[PDB]
Image (cartoon, rainbow over all chains, first blue to last red; front, side):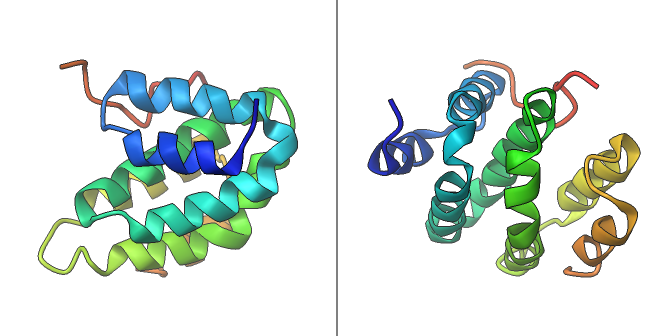
Length: 127
Length: 12
């Protein structure tokens, strides 16, 4: 049963494990009908998380964007109007840290072509 | 502790 305030909770609980990301990402696709609200609160809780978890949020994005595609172009569509902000935001606050994992996520994105060429760019130059 | 998420794990 979808509820915005439950998502905020799951997000708060999201760990870095392969299991945490992969079954939270399943919950979200179950509710692909709620893609717009889901992404908008992800964007809010993302910006609230500490820097060590910001990456993990982008890895949630990944697993839902990629697996939602067998189901429809909802989250794919919802996330683009956001990702140029989320990346550019996480680029900073990686002030005293490493942007190599973000530059790889863009590369496994143009490789699998999850988004399109001009948008993988702007994602690259957002940082 | 479980294995760490890998961005590639999704099926392509």
